[PDB]
Amino acid sequence: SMKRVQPCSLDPATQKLITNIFSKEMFKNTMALMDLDVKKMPLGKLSKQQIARGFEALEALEEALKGPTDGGQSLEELSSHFYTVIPHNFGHSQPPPINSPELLQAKKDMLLVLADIELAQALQAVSEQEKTVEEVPHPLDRDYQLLKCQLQLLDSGAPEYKVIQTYLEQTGSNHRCPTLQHIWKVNQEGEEDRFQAHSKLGNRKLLWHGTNMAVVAAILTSGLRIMPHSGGRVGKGIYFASENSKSAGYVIGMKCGAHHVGYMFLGEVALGREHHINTDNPSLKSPPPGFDSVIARGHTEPDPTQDTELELDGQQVVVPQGQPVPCPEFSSSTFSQSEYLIYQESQCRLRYLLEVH
Ligand SMILES: C[C@H](NC(=O)CCc1nc2ccccc2c(=O)[nH]1)c1ccccc1
């Protein structure tokens, strides 16, 4: 017989969030923005095997880019294999050869996003328990439940609301700052325990992490992650910024009606003893011995004299509130704005999610 659909328990803002982060249109938009052939790679067809085969093909390119010339297959031939595994669309012209470190990392990053899209699809698979029960949750409750992540919408007068708003406003773009729509407190439990393990580290800061909308569901289910092919200017870690405007550059939003909707995280990061750098080092896989984080220091930093603190689970967590000011020691840094790196997933726990227009 027909199953009852129970009424949705979620507030309107949370329903919109849930709709957005599981939206098939959103996921396909994201694949189009990454030059993927959505006709050849429908969401239902995405598989862990294909994604692994994709990374294998990129691993062969990487070896060709580094270690020869030694009689291996040409970059063209190796590129062609990759494009067979992971179909791309360049207006049905031939896709281009993956013949630089930059392009190799860009393709690795594309596959990391695609892997989180596939995660979201796999998460939504209907269980046998669900086929047998005679009543089902509203689809949005079901999707929310799949995250195994508590989201609590804040209002204006929550203790931390003004602190968060100030952090956004003071360190966001001066001319056209993202407009704050909603903040949710994020409690992904089973993040709590591994995070407790760094309770000794006094130097905690609440930092920005901007992402593709297509990876928000994955992050809510599993936290911020370091994957085998993660990389960037400061190597294989989790990247954060103290300046919203830096992180905002990584937000991939979506046009909805007359607005552009984007999501940004704030994580509590146990930075411990910081190692400061002033030139790019893509080879890093941990801080130097004796250090707990690497901070690629920018020409500017939110003015430290305006820092405040929030008390999160009884630990003081620094929250910048100042506009960015120059840091003379780092005026010649290769970095305009700071990038904060950790190399263990346990050193971050998600605290807030912001919707910005
Ligand atoms: C490729 C994508 N990476 C990101 O979402 C990180 C984006 C990001 N990079 C930064 C770099 C320097 C400073 C700040 C940031 C940031 O806020 N986000 C990814 C990484 C792993 C799994 C799924 C997706």
Image (cartoon, helix red, strand yellow):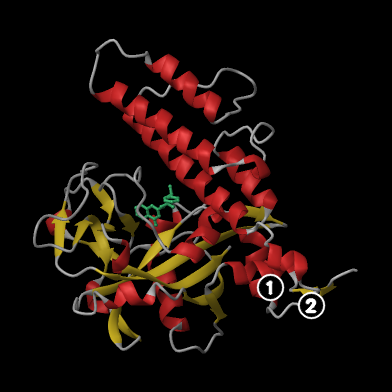
- Which circle marks residue 6 in the picture? 2
Residue 312 place in picture, x, y as percent: 35, 84
The quadrant of the picture occupied by the C terminus is bottom right
Residue, x 35% and y 42% (percent of image)? 229
Observer-nearest of 179 and 80: 80
Left or right of 286: which side holds 220? right
Observer-nearest of 21 and 139: 139
The answer for how far apart the CA atoms under marks 1 and 2 are is: 9 Å
Residue, x 19% and y 53% (percent of image)? 286
Instruction: Please say if the residues under marks 1 and 2 sit with CB atoms less than 8 Å apart.
Output: yes
The quadrant of the picture occupied by the N terminus is bottom right
Residue, x 33% and y 56% (percent of image)? 239
Occupied quadrant, residue 222: bottom left
Q: Secondary structure at mark 1?
A: helix
Amino acid of disc 1: Asp
Q: From the Cβ of disc 2, is ligand 1 less than 8 Å away?
A: no
Occupied quadrant, residue 58: top left
Q: Is residue 226 above or below residue 87?
A: below
- Which circle marks residue 141 in the picture? 1
Residue 142 place in picture, x, y as percent: 68, 69
Left or right of 320: which side holds 209? right
Residue 311 place in picture, x, y as percent: 33, 87
